[PDB]
Image (cartoon, rainbow, N blue to C red):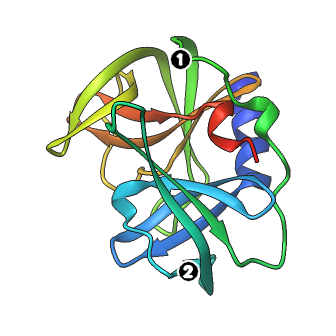
Amino acid sequence: MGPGFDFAQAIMKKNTVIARTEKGEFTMLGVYDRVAVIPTHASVGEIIYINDVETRVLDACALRDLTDTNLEITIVKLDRNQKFRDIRHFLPRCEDDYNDAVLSVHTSKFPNMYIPVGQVTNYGFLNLGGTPTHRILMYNFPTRAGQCGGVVTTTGKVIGIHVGGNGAQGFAAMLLHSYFTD
């Protein structure tokens, strides 16, 4: 409907796959080459389904900060025959607050879903399902089961992936440029 939704759509159409693990179906953001991200609670194993194709996992790393605190991001390298468009130049370098974000989801349950979530707070610490978690972004939208892995964007930036909610608010793990240097 506007430039925010234009940016969100441009990312969803080229840089997302549907990932399935034994813990469900997730939106998965492809970042560059065969490297993608997913919430750590997806419990990625040695095999994952990518758009319903059995795919070997070449590497999976559950990120933690330098206090050894969960960040709820897992970086996955997929044994896929095709590379993602490189979007690392759209990743922020620092933790920040944002205006006017969109959360976008693409699964069997919720295809082509876009939500204007408004203002995004650098919330920081969250006890997420009983796990102390850092670098959390918060938006005031009643997000529901099925939205985990959803991409959080502003115009020109990919800032996070949706990892939880409390019924009134939604929570995303920060994406930072420094996660994806090679």
How far from the left and from the top, in percent, is residue 20? 48, 74
Above or below, 172 against 130 in this view is above
How far from the left and from the top, in percent, is residue 59? 59, 69
Q: Quadrant of residue 114?
A: top right
Report the residue marked by disc 2. Answer: 49
Point out the image quarter for the N terminus. Answer: top right
Q: Which label sits in the foreground, 2 or 1?
A: 1
In the rendered structure, find residue 174 and report the number of the disc placed on it.
none
Report the residue marked by disc 1. Answer: 95
Above or below, 75 against 59 in this view is above
Label 2 sits on what residue type? Tyr
User: Total number of numbered labels?
Assistant: 2
Q: Identify which residue is drawn at 55% across, 80% down.
A: 49
Query: Which is nearer the eye, 66 or 144?
Result: 66
Q: Residues within 10 Å of mark 1 (few under 14, many from 20)?
A: some
Res. 2 visible in picture: no
N-terminal of the pair, mark 2 or mark 1, is 2
Above or below, 155 against 170 in this view is above
Dot 2 lies on which element?
strand
Query: Which is nearer the eye, 118 or 94?
Result: 94
Q: Identify which residue is drawn at 61% across, 53% down.
A: 112
The residue most toward the bottom is 54
How far from the left and from the top, in percent, is residue 98? 55, 13
Label 1 sits on what residue type? Glu
Q: Identify which residue is drawn at 29% across, 35% down.
A: 133
Tags 2 and 1 touching, CB below 8 Å: no
Res. 162 visible in picture: yes
